[PDB]
Image 1 (cartoon, chains in turn green, orange):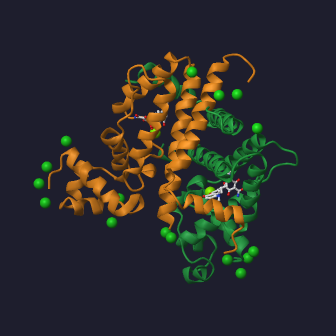
Image 2 (tube, rainbow over the protein chains, first blue to last red; image 1 turned 135 degrees about the vertical axis):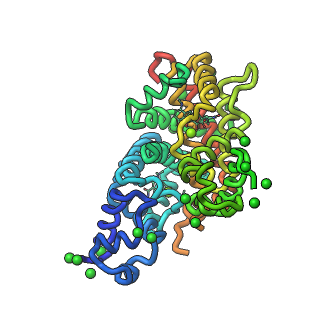
Image 3 (cartoon, rainbow over the protein chains, first blue to last red; image 1 turned 30 degrees about the vertical axis):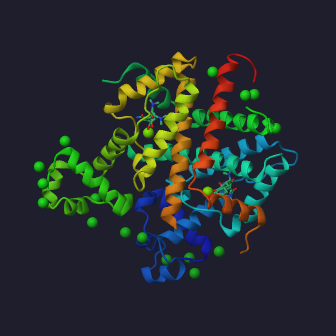
Length: 199
Length: 199
Ligand SMILES: CN(C)c1ccc(O)c2c1C[C@H]1C[C@H]3[C@H](N(C)C)C(O)=C(C(N)=O)C(=O)[C@@]3(O)C(O)=C1C2=O
Ligand SMILES: CN(C)c1ccc(O)c2c1C[C@H]1C[C@H]3[C@H](N(C)C)C(O)=C(C(N)=O)C(=O)[C@@]3(O)C(O)=C1C2=O
Ligand SMILES: [Cl-]
Ligand SMILES: [Cl-]
Ligand SMILES: [Cl-]
Ligand SMILES: [Cl-]
Ligand SMILES: [Cl-]
Ligand SMILES: [Cl-]
Ligand SMILES: [Cl-]
Ligand SMILES: [Cl-]
Ligand SMILES: [Cl-]
Ligand SMILES: [Cl-]
Ligand SMILES: [Cl-]
Ligand SMILES: [Cl-]
Ligand SMILES: [Cl-]
Ligand SMILES: [Cl-]
Ligand SMILES: [Cl-]
Ligand SMILES: [Cl-]
Ligand SMILES: [Mg+2]
Ligand SMILES: [Mg+2]
């Protein structure tokens, strides 16, 4: 079938949902596309190159809150941005593992730059803004990775542990994520407002 | 060579450092142990079973701050516990990926129970204590995963991005982790002390 970049991406994302990240192979992608492996190679050099592109395109397609609304507080931006990142990562099987290890692509530079500048315009030093943005990124990835990989992995319990596992087996991870996110953001705010004061 | 559980673990951890998680195979472990594959199978049924055991034994061996010191504040316990978890995860190649998706083993039940009880003794509801413990776990995993997988993965840059990448390429991830961790813990404290007050 059609082997423009868009269509190759499309097929690889469909395959990802079917196979997961470990099971995804270029041979299987060629099959899906109805082509021979050497044909695919002209378009897609290896699995690494494919995964890198998927990580970018999943966010381009589905991460809609990359930038602050006009007049938005930095707190609200980080909240909305994290929720959006989370959702985008969850949209595909093993989507957080596809993201893991990547760094901002040229196609995301202006976006990331804007996020950093926004933080510095709201009183963060570049370093402190970086630490905030990384912490949210790490927390969000971590939460989604554990959600997705725990699902992939699937009476002498002591009572709090039994109960805590009953709580966890009762939603998908969202409540715990959102509560953690609030804690994170509030801590960032306490730090920012402290300036040079012992806190 | 010797195929007691300890020695099999030992060899698998050595192999993990040599191959990484994706490259680790039972066939390669049998080679390392100087045995044939059917011999290994008696001891180790599959890679999953092996990884599960490694995740447990890495913490048993090297995560020394599972429990609060006598009289320790909950804040200090979470800090020390997170630092210890982080270090243990970093001790082996792809160590955070080995941990990912696991849940507490029978051999960790008393430990995890104690952590939960400790939080509830310090004023947390079980749910709020769970959310704190999960948030620290997720943040720590996320940070280490990104550190380890970014290393595994290894001029039109805009200036803040260029600068931020210079900052990141200057330590291993520790400074950003520790700063984030403080933000997280302080947010937990603001929440705990609020009780039923709008905050
Ligand atoms: C320079 N910049 C801080 C870095 C450095 C190394 C990194 O590994 C990363 C960044 C930017 C962050 C921005 C975060 C942002 N957010 C805090 C989740 C984000 O919304 C985006 C985005 N493209 O909209 C990211 O790329 C991002 O998810 C991401 O993957 C990043 C990331 O991987
Ligand atoms: C019931 N309990 C809260 C759960 C439920 C699901 C989970 O997936 C987990 C826990 C306990 C947490 C405790 C955390 C703890 N810490 C906050 C990092 C920890 O120190 C240990 C430990 N064994 O000392 C964990 O097992 C732990 O790393 C872990 O892997 C957990 C984990 O995987
Ligand atoms: Cl065709
Ligand atoms: Cl076609
Ligand atoms: Cl074509
Ligand atoms: Cl195209
Ligand atoms: Cl492949
Ligand atoms: Cl294949
Ligand atoms: Cl503020
Ligand atoms: Cl405070
Ligand atoms: Cl031998
Ligand atoms: Cl021997
Ligand atoms: Cl033996
Ligand atoms: Cl033994
Ligand atoms: Cl294997
Ligand atoms: Cl092999
Ligand atoms: Cl307190
Ligand atoms: Cl406050
Ligand atoms: Mg990223
Ligand atoms: Mg765990």
